Length: 139
Ligand SMILES: NC(=O)[C@H]1CCCN(C(=O)[C@@H]2SCc3cccnc32)C1
Ligand SMILES: [Zn+2]
Image 1: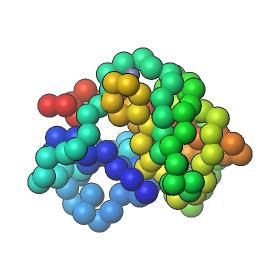
Image 2: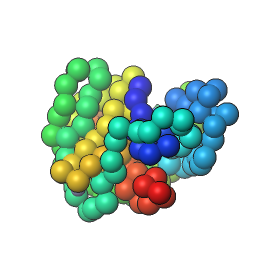
Image 3: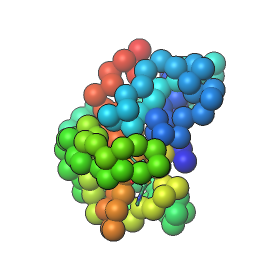
């Protein structure tokens, strides 16, 4: 679990969005596993606007942060799960690192700010949904 809170927006994995997220929907994209909802309180986070490919993510299944090298956002095949059919997920970045079911929502940050959130994983892989292209989060 986990979310980004920036301005009057809350960014979560679309597959973990709550009834309240959907009732205050701003934007969602199943192909990216992202959903943004509106908030009444001002958010605590700031978004990176950069091309970094290294950073640090929070892994809830280890209660620890790990450094990662990750690929540029791209279209990657993701196997079927209870949440989605087998499909290509866009704006996804892969890295070698631990992740397991429950770790989605953990933040990936570089020196500039929040880069994205955990969205997929595999045998020693972790995948992050990029948010750096969502310029409107800052306005
Ligand atoms: N974006 C998606 O389509 C997700 C939806 C939830 C299930 N998916 C996963 O990858 C799980 S959750 C993190 C993790 C880590 C190791 C193995 N499996 C997983 C795919
Ligand atoms: Zn950066």
